[PDB]
Image (cartoon, rainbow, N blue to C red; front, side, top):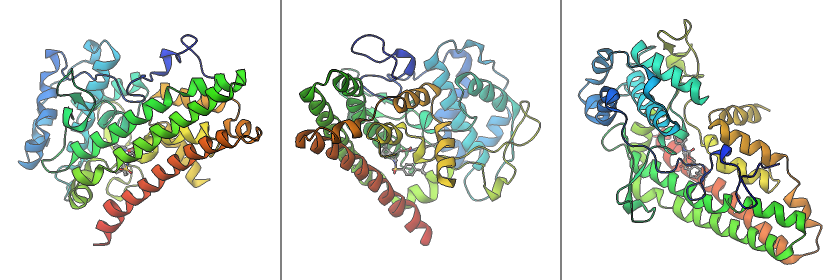
Length: 354
Ligand SMILES: C#Cc1ccc(NC(=O)OC[C@]23CN(S(=O)(=O)c4ccc(C(C)(C)C)cc4)C[C@H]2C[C@H]2C[C@@H]3C2(C)C)cc1
């Protein structure tokens, strides 16, 4: 099922890092000088939006060809830059004054880069979290204190807390993802202890991931998230403010609908749903958000689905330790889902009631 680079490590074609998992390892922070005008706007989005200067600034940009973005990391940075500018341009200050046409000198390079990466031309999780970070000190570990985001939308939008805590959850889960190949090898070799320890390691990492997730409350304010950050994560699919979608000037003639952010864009949920065998209007939206994940990660999720069932192997062994380790994994994953639902309630549904 899962293609392997060697006897120990999954194929590099899945673009999954041993240390940070689905996150992009050591993201590029600076683009070639050729793109300084894009970088300036993105680096100054807070003060450009607040001063009402962002849209005029974007409308004065020249056309910059994407031909000089010659590797994956520079293209991912550029997608993040152009995606943040796009959200800022469409929604503005978030009072209802929206733009229905994205200017061509952003829309064309953005859409071509999106085609290259096979991502939709709208900000997604893989941009604003998985690639939107850096280490303050390269010699220190991956901790909140030692990390920052590359871009925010508004001063006080809590985007650092929201994005970095999400990223640290993904990094915690990375230590579980790297055990997945060991789980399937242990099943094939009928290695009881190897499988038990793999399942206990996955459980322990997902439990840690929930403890990292708990940090969200200390770095994100519900009012600022609901009334500010949520705006720039909103899309134009089923949105009455952009009922037909957005016109990408110079790329498509007709407006096009693309969805805003969703927790379904994290590959962590489907990865361990499938691994543990615990995976329709909801099924259609689920599958759609899969298409908002990096294509290599979709392919990893598919290969996982092609393997034998961990759950049926474990429950056939009359083995309490194996079943308890399996159950600990399920419990951990359910607790992450349950916590996501709590965050949706405290940071969206409640603020909306008010
Ligand atoms: C573009 C874009 C865009 C921006 C951000 C996100 N965030 C995202 O996918 O986060 C995954 C989370 C889930 N949340 S959450 O706080 O419950 C959360 C709740 C609500 C949202 C939206 C609807 C506002 C987008 C996002 C997140 C944090 C993460 C922690 C754990 C649970 C999963 C996890 C990694 C396994 C998605 C699209």
